[PDB]
Amino acid sequence: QTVPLSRLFDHAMLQAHRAHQLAIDTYQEFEETYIPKDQKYSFLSFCFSDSIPTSNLELLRISLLLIESWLEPVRFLRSMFANNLVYDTSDSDDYHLLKDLEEGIQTLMGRLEQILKQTYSKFDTDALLKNYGLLYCFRKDMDKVETFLRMVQCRSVEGSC
């Protein structure tokens, strides 16, 4: 057996949905815990996803870039949820889920047959407001990924949508 394209899209869409939920859940939990009323949305500081607006190996290509920009910051997500805690390198969060998604996208690309590098700062132990902005962009980027993958799925797998 060879994996149908649909299963491949179904796997990638579930993992994008899950990365996107992770981003939403983390942002919310941060905001509720650390951001007072008077500072809500203070971040408003452009996200990777604000670069390219709105079928293609291209859409898949951007998705891939978006995920890649987060693969390293992501292990540090829970480090902000303590007081003076630095991530101890213990199992590559359950959040290298992005590595799963990454490879799932690179698999979809080789089925469907770069001058500027865009990398995110690392999360911190100002710092609060940076971490806030970073969580905002992780959420915006993951929404974009899920979006661009759906567009591709629909056009590539008939009846999908």
Image (cartoon, rainbow, N blue to C red):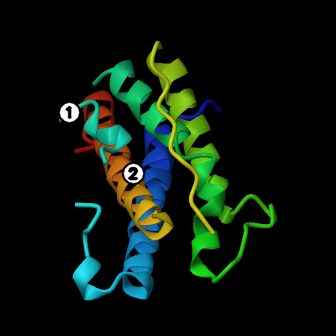
**Residue 48 as seen in the image, left or right of residue 72:** left
Q: Could you say which is closer to the camera, residue 21 or residue 52?
A: 52
Give the SS element for disc 1: loop
Q: Quadrant of the N terminus?
A: top right
Residue type beneath disc 1: Pro
Q: Is residue 113 above or below residue 75?
A: above
Q: Earlier in the sequence, mark 2 or mark 1?
A: 1
Quadrant in the picture for residue 116: top left
Residue 85 position, x and y percent, is 71, 76
Residue 125's label in the rendered image is none
Residue 35 position, x and y percent, is 36, 81
Q: Which residue is mark 2?
A: 142
Toward the left, the furthest residue is: 54
**Residue 50 as seen in the image, left or right of residue 16:** left
Q: Which residue is mark 1?
A: 53
| Residue at position x 58%, y 65% in the image | 77
